[PDB]
Length: 204
Ligand SMILES: CC(C)(C)c1ccc(C(=O)Nc2nnc3n2CCS3)cc1
Ligand SMILES: [Zn+2]
Image (cartoon, rainbow, N blue to C red; front, top):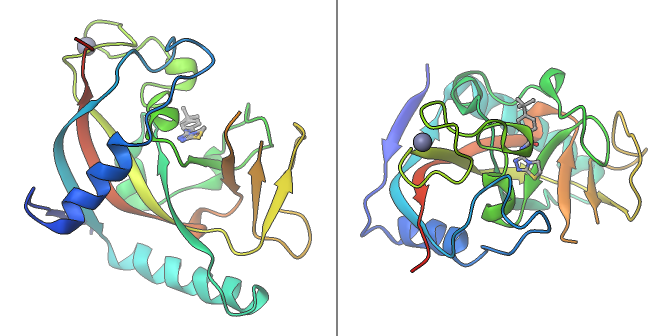
């Protein structure tokens, strides 16, 4: 099944992913309620997910999208957080477990900003936080999030909240607008490329 490759801190690839993660921390409108308070992550581990069934399904989808998007994937690296990352890296994304409460409909959601996704690591609104301390801003418990290859194909820009079950005709994804949220409606338009294990760090 799924094989995890551990990246070394010396690898440029490691240093790019951590750079994307550290440099996209923002202040969120809920004052850090869901995701905690921090200016930095402490990155513990970065692992590359290798799964043959999933790579195959991703590629397949990727080709269909290319055809309808002038032979462009429009692939982006985006974050995703969920308390079921473990099911994700073994069975892929599953739109049947879509974010029912999502602003732009029932799809699978991704962020440019790591701090956005981190808000969903323990559940929606941050849930009741970590299992041990029930603390959404815990600094001890290890969190995991995904930095994913996401096939956006042709994106539809939505500036209003609106329940969508699927992308608009001729489109493969929705970009919704504070900051943009990227939504896909098919699980195979995302591959969980990097599994990041980390902590949020208490500001000094
Ligand atoms: C399994 C349950 C708890 C239903 C679930 C529901 C929604 C999400 C999710 O959408 N997470 C996420 N990661 N990055 C972003 N988001 C949404 C904003 S941008 C993850 C898990
Ligand atoms: Zn904890």
